[PDB]
Length: 320
Length: 320
Ligand SMILES: Nc1nc2c(ncn2[C@@H]2O[C@H](COP(=O)(O)OP(=O)(O)O)[C@@H](O)[C@H]2O)c(=O)[nH]1
Ligand SMILES: Nc1nc2c(ncn2[C@@H]2O[C@H](COP(=O)(O)OP(=O)(O)O)[C@@H](O)[C@H]2O)c(=O)[nH]1
Ligand SMILES: [Mg+2]
Ligand SMILES: [Mg+2]
Ligand SMILES: [Mg+2]
Ligand SMILES: [Mg+2]
Image (cartoon, rainbow over all chains, first blue to last red; front, side, top):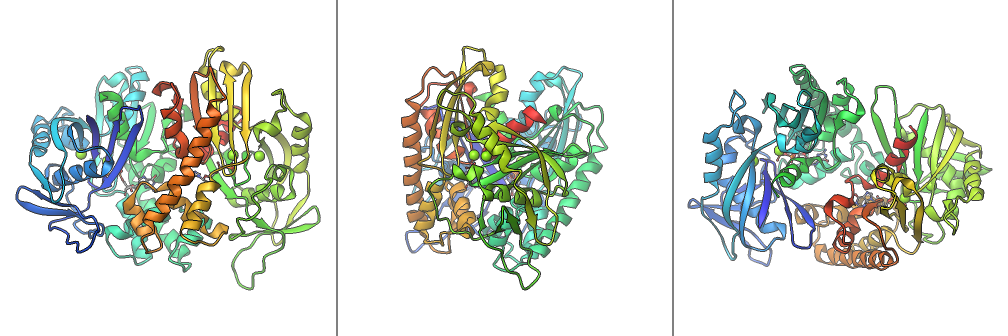
């Protein structure tokens, strides 16, 4: 079995194909604590051991430690989160080959050439042995690594003439990464990674507006408000009974304005692109400003409506 | 201004393009009551008059009256719902030209030829004069009518050879309609409309499982549960604090099995199609069973991840 894994530091996205020809997409969050969970009843908990440390999936992990999520790519917790995503995907426990991801500035050095040291480091990370209490864990065999961004734009890149170029804008949970690649993948023109802002900027604003606990527990409510920010009818029913709808709508717009200004400022660093694509979980939050501020015809502007999965699907289309 | 309007009896979907080139999509429900709403405070309410009757947008309209929604297409309420959709879209009040829809079996007679009488009736419905209390209403000038289903598959159909044919499966709020069209729109091979089941079957099952009020108010909670039915993490936080996650999950699965069995039974009435497309708000609910049970390669199976808008987007691509 071959599983494509975009192991982001906010959510692990999986994609694979079964025997009946159905193509499956699964998402599991990066939310673990460094201790086992205690269950006195029949609640299922997931308690792991890796490198001699205990970890467990935590549904209310604190939104804390909003720092270096680059180190996370080579961490013990990353190994746990990937195993946890596999364990909760619905696939049967088996040996699996996988293809994982490295952020553009980790996969590539400043010369836009493969950073072999990081690529190997990433593969080695998955050899760390893991155990699950009360169950069998999948076994990771072959590990291939793809860079983020490019796989998402590959289908389009194949169609572009070599002198044309696609600008791929990825807004993730904690970072905003942009790359410009020549048609038919004939070269990387520029990569600009930015780890100062992500969708969590908006999520944090929402949780502050509604004074929600700063944990994973309230992440769902916050995302729903954001996703349905333009539907008063939905907001009317969801918002914690009251009508702080005004104050939340306000906080959202402010964070969104920040994201939009950042992308437009960084966009000015790029030139000569002929096509534009916006991906990642936060794509819908910045697509309008980007389209408005680029001189690119509709026909050459790409955004799907399943953006958080654009990368892993591109990876699957390439390697499956 | 030209607005594309898929005026379905569950939701009105709008699509248009302004000046900056941004393409806008808006959704507004069909939920009105036959009397004005009273507001003693500053809560905005929309009170209309049309054909000599008062109607008002009602956020908690009873889910009742699951009988004939076909007549709704030529009703006074349909005129109000469309004006209400326009009033809440963000567009400025003005004269507008529009293109609306008629269900396949209303647009076409049993010989699969245009039912001019229904087409004219639809156009005339919009000449009914409407008034809003406390504000101005849009003025509808030119009215064009497109049939449902075909516009959604038009992009693909243009690419098909004349001997090939696309099967378009549309699961809406209260109906499931299927059509088979020859490549390059070279003829309609078959239309099978079914008014006995829709997405509301699953919604109703969910409301009964959580004992929610049978009104529009709980529609949002019900749809979220369905949409996130495969995410225990999200369900854990959303379900009315309890743990009927088993019992609601149970009810959904049975309603979904009923929808899947119906589509598959109706599919056996069609043959010779080479490509399949699944659309409508309920597309994600039956796509797997349909893919599983057709002998059509991945490359010839079409499903977007914005299914409730496939038809109006197709309409817009044709006439904008
Ligand atoms: N507003 C919005 N947020 C989304 C959408 N899809 C996913 N997200 C969220 O956007 C954030 C970014 O997730 P993702 O890009 O997958 O990134 P990662 O783990 O850094 O790769 C997450 O918190 C997601 O839950 C969407 O359609 N709209
Ligand atoms: N499960 C699910 N329901 C959806 C989705 N998009 C829309 N819906 C719902 O599906 C139902 C059908 O809506 P729609 O097809 O637009 O039909 P209509 O007004 O009869 O045309 C509505 O209750 C929508 O809220 C989706 O992605 N998933
Ligand atoms: Mg990512
Ligand atoms: Mg990764
Ligand atoms: Mg419809
Ligand atoms: Mg209609």
